[PDB]
Amino acid sequence: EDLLKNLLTMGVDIDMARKRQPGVFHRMITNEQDLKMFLLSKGASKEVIASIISRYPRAITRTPENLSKRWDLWRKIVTSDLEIVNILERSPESFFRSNNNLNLENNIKFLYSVGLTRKCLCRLLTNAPRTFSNSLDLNKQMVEFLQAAGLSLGHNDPADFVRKIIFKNPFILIQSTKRVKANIEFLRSTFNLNSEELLVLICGPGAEILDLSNDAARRSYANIKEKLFSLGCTEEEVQKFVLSYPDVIFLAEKKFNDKIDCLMEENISISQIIENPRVLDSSISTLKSRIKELVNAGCNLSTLNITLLSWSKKRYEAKLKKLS
DNA sequence: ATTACCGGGCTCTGCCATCTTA
DNA sequence: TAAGATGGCAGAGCCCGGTAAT
Ligand SMILES: [K+]
Image (cartoon, rainbow, N blue to C red; front, side, top):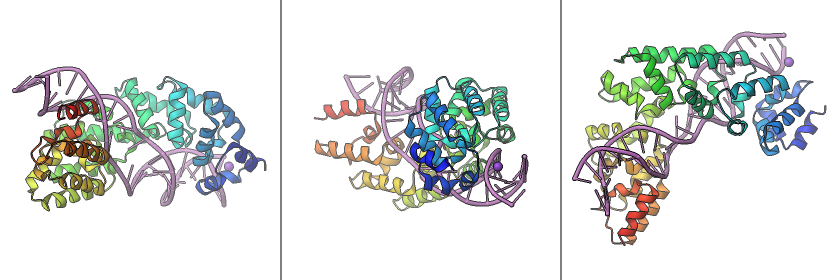
């Protein structure tokens, strides 16, 4: 009865809430008051509170005791209340989609038990919160799958493969095993690719590749291949290029292309580009802004050493001065 | 005094489908 | 027997600078 009124004064988007979790609105008891007070208690602005509820209405079904206990467990990993407010604003669902604090506590035990440091649990919680709402078994699955995948390739102690990858790729424990398998076999196939090459690739520069959704990797590589072929680069060169800079698989196809095109419209050859893959770190805006500045001076770009295009502001700005 | 090499810092939700659970 | 709990999916970059090399 009193439910819609409170939410309305709270700033909530009621129509949106009802669409996401209609069920919640057919309960006779809801604790929307205690939650407001609870988050207010921990420093959340009223606008955040509304935003959290607008996106995860079920949040209002939790009791002060539960909320307080879950919060204190997060504070076993994160150090300030503010850190947690921020995470919840960014992703409500991770905190509120479960109310099994025992399970949560077991995740924390398990993850410690795998040999991860607190800075590593902190990193996980901060950037991949939803890790801690996983079932214990689900986190166990992924960990067992990595160990198995560690030894299924030539790794000396899998225990440490797990730590390296989980540190380099914080988002791995919120991916399905299905998905991460398919991304590994995608790399193994498309490129050489013997166990050791593969292993560094996964731990180092191609670590983010394991998070790509189904076939989005395959599809984004296809585009790379076409667009580079079209410009006169051979498959070898395409492979060499992408392996020396796998980040390029994460770009939206359209971005890659526009990026390639903005560079080349200025008479920078496809050759300069793939022998200096990092120029592609820069957003298109930055590239575009820098291109303007240099051609504005006496630079011809056709023959310049274009590495500066992806230098830091400092080093770039310094060098631009010197050119004029 | 200048650039290359390379790794690190940031960084991941919001939706739907299929169970459990009471 | 309807909600709650849980799993899984699509979508996706940019920047900085230490230190080696010259
Ligand atoms: K109920």
